Image 1: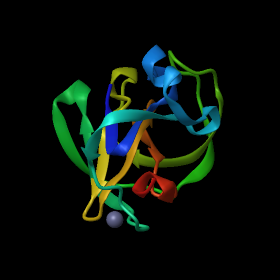
Image 2: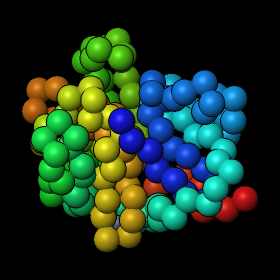
Image 3: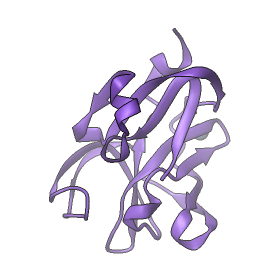
Image 4: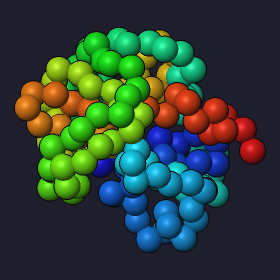
Length: 140
Ligand SMILES: [Zn+2]
């Protein structure tokens, strides 16, 4: 589990979005596993605006933050998980590291702020849904 709180936006994995998120929907994309909902309260998270490929992510299943190198956001084939079939996922960054389904929502951060959230796992890789291209999260 986990979310990004930027301005009046809540960013979550689409597969973990609640009824309240859908009832306050701003934007969603299945291919990216992202959904954004509107919030009453101001969030303080800063979204990274950068092309960093090193950062730190939170792994709930190990109660640890791990420094990682990660690929640039790409269209990648993802094997079946407990929450998605085998399919292509877009805007996905991969690192070597641990990721269980419950780790989805863990933040990946670089010196510039929040890069993305854990979205995929398996075969000793962790995949992150990038948010750094969603420049509109910074405004409205
Ligand atoms: Zn950065």
